[PDB]
Image: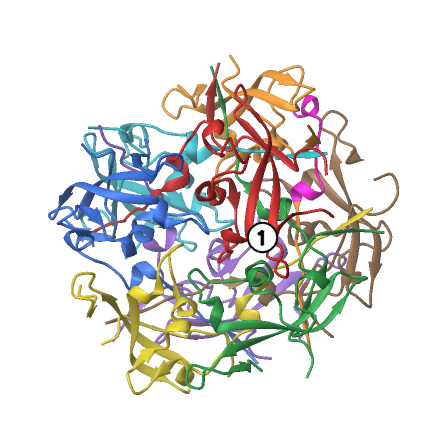
Chain colours: A orange, B brown, C yellow, D green, E purple, F blue, G red, H cyan
Amino acid sequence: ISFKPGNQIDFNRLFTLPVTELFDPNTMFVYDQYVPLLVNLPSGFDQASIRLKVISYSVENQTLGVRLEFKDPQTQQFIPVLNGPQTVFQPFNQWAD
Amino acid sequence: ISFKPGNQIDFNRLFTLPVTELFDPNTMFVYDQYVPLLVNLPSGFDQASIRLKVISYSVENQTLGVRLEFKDPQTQQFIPVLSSTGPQTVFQPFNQWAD
Amino acid sequence: ISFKPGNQIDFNRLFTLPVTELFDPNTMFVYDQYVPLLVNLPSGFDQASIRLKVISYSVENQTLGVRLEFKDPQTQQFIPVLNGPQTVFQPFNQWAD
Amino acid sequence: ISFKPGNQIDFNRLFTLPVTELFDPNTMFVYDQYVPLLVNLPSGFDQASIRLKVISYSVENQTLGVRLEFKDPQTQQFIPVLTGPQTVFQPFNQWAD
Amino acid sequence: ISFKPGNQIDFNRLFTLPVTELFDPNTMFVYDQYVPLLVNLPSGFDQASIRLKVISYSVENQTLGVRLEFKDPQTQQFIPVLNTGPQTVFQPFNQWAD
Amino acid sequence: ISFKPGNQIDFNRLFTLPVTELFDPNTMFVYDQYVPLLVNLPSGFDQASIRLKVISYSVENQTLGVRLEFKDPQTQQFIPVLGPQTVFQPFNQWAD
Amino acid sequence: ISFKPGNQIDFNRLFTLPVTELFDPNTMFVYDQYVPLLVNLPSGFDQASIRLKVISYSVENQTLGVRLEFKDPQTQQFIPVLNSTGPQTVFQPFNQWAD
Amino acid sequence: ISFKPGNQIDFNRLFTLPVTELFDPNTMFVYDQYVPLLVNLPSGFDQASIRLKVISYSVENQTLGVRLEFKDPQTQQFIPVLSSTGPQTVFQPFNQWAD
C-alpha cells in the first residue's frame, strides 16, 4: 500500500584512493581506468583522445598537479588542452582542517 | 499544428529483481551486469575495474550490504578500498511496495 | 559503521489528477497551482507572468492541448505567443490498454 | 601558473535533522521550510498549494510515512490525492550499526 | 569587447526515425544502436546483457510497445522480466501532428 | 497492463518573444519577469540583487547585448559582473 | 531552413569575487545574496531559513571555512546544525588562476 | 573535523578550439573525437553510429552549420536524417570573447 523508494549508491561513497596511487610512476600519466574519475567527461567521449600527465602532487593536501592533453586529429600528437602543473585539484573528498 | 513530445523510458520502469538474484551465492559477488544498476558510476568509467562483495542481505527488506573492491593497476588483483569487517553501505536497490 | 543513503521523493510518485481537474472550464485556463507541474519553468521564473489556455482535451487518453499566454509588462494584459494548440501531451503517467 | 577549480557545496553535506524535528507534533504536518528538502519540487511550484501529513515515523530507522494533500482550486480546502501513508522513506543519509 | 556564450546541440534536434526503422522486422528486436535512445541507461551499463522486444507498433501514432529481456547471468540465456503484452507503450520521438 | 509515460513540457516549446519586448525602452533594463529566462539562476537566488542593462539589440538576428549588474551588499549600488559585456540570442530561431 | 538554438547567460560561471568580499566583516556571516551561489540549494528551498557563519578564510588559497545555521521553526531563532569547534566545511567557492 | 570537497576537472569548460580545427577539410566531417563535445549524446550511445557533416562555417562568428548522418543497421552505410541542401543546425560550439 506504501511506496518505498530504492537507491543507487554514488561512487564517491564507496571509492577513494591516496593521490600517489592514481598514476603510473614509470610513465607519470594517470592510469587510464582513473581518467573518468578525475575528469567529468561528456557521454560517449573517446578517452583514447586524452591523457593526464602528473607534474606534481601533495600527500598533505591530497592534490594532483596535472597537464591535461588531447590528441590533435591533424598531427596525431598529444598537445596541452590549456594553451609546470597546469591544473591543480583535489580528486576526492577529504576530512581534515 | 501541435507539438507532441516523445519519451525515453527510465530503466527502473522496466527492470526489477529480488536482492537474492543480484549476486552469485557461491562467490558472494554481485553479478557484473548489475554493478552499473546498483552504483552510480561516473561517465565513461569502466565497470571491469571494480566488483561488489555482498556482506549481508535481507529478503524481508530487499536490501544489500556491500563492500567495493577495485583492480590494483600494478598487480591486476582485486583489493578492498582502504572496512576490515562489515559492509561499507546498506541500501535497497529497487523501489518496493509493501508498508 | 554502514552508510544508508537517504531519499527525496519525486513529486510524480505522490501526485496525479484527471485532466478535467487541471483547468477551470469557465475560463479554459489551467489553474495557476498546476502550471509549474505541466511546464518545466526556468529556475526563478514567476508563474504569475504566464497562463495556459486549454484548446483541447481527451478523457479517454488523459491528454491536454495547450497554448501559452504571457502578461504584457506595459499593458498588464495577457497576450498569446504568436509564431489550434501549440502542444498536445499526457501530463501524468497512465496504466491502460 | 596553475588553474585551481572552485566548488559549490551540496546542501546535504551541511544539513541533517532527526525525523521528529521535521514536523509539528500537534498537527502532524511537515514544517513548511522542510517540504522542499523531502520532496523534489518542480521549478516555481507554489508550496502554499500542498502540505505533507505525517502518518507514521520511526526513530530507530529515521524514516517518515507521509501522505500529500493539495489545495482544491474551487473550495480552497486541502484534500488527499488518493488509510496509511503514500510513501515511507528515509529523508537524510544515516550511518548505522 | 563582448562575451558570446557557446552551446552544445541536443541530440533530439538532429535525429528522428519512423518507428518501423527502429527494429529488425525478422526478429522483432530493437537494433542495438537505438536501445540507448529509447531507454535511459545507467552510466557504464553493459548493453549486451539486455534486449528490447517489439510487441506492437503504430505507424499512425509513431508509438512502440516494448518488453525488456535480460541475459540470465548463470545460464547466459535471455529471459523476460517477471512475466503477454508490452511492458510499456510510448512515442520515442517528438512529432508534429494536425 | 502497459505503462504509458507522461510528460512535462519544456518552456522553450511554448514561449518565445521578439527581443524588443524583453526590456522597458524608457530605462533600457530587461523587465524583471524575463531576467530568469535570459540568465540561468541558481536555486533560491534573490533576483532583486541583479539587473540586466540592454546596450544593443538586433531585430534581424534576434540578439541582445546586455550588461549584467549586481548590487554591492556593502554599499547598495549596482556594479557590472565582469559596449556590451554579453551578446546572446535568448530564444531558438529558424533562419537562412 | 536552419535551426539556431537560443542560450542563457550562465550566472555562476561568470560571477567571481575575492573571498573577503563574500561576508560581512562585522557579523562574520556570508551576505544573504551570495548564499545560493556558494551552496547548491534544493528547488524551492527558502534561503531566508539559513545562514552561513564564516569561521576561517584564506586570502592566499581563496577558501572559506563555514558553519551552517538554520532558523528553528518553533523558536524562530538561528541554531547551528549539530548531529562546536571549527568549520563544518572548508572550500574554494570560485575558480582560481594562482602562481 | 572539516569537510573538504573533492572536484573533477570539467573537460567541456576547459576545452576550446577555433571552428576550422573541428573538422577534416578534405571530407568536411567533424573529427570523430569532437562529436560528443558538440552534441549532448544519450547515456551509452555509440558515437561510431553517427557523423556530423559540415555544410557551412564562419571564422568571424566561430559557428558551424551541420547535418547529422547515421549508420543504417542493415547496409552499414551512412545515410542523412530526413534531399536537403542546407544545414540542420547553425551553432557556436564554444564561448567567445570576440569584438
Question: What is the x, y in percent for residue A79?
Answer: 44, 19
Left or right: residue D57 versus residue C21 is right
Question: What is the x, y in percent for residue E63?
Answer: 42, 72
For residue E59, what is the image quadrant? bottom left
**Most distant residue in the left direction:** F60
Which residue sits at x=67%, y=76%? D85
The answer to whether any part of residue D71 appears in the image is: yes
Nearest to the observer: residue E3 or residue D15: D15
Which residue sits at x=67%, y=51%? D16
* First to last magenta residue range: A11-22
Which residue sits at x=82%, y=68%? B60
- Residue type at mark 1: give it: Pro
Q: Is residue A12 magenta?
A: yes
For residue E78, what is the image quadrant? bottom right
Nearest to the observer: residue F71 or residue G95: F71
**In this view, D29 is above or below A76:** below
**In this view, H38 is above or below B10:** above
Left or right: residue C53 versus residue G95 is left
- Counting the numbered discs, the total is 1
Q: Provide the residue designation for mark 1.
A: E42
Question: What is the x, y in percent for residue A83?
Answer: 39, 18
**In this view, D64 is above or below G64:** below
Q: Secondary structure at mark 1?
A: loop
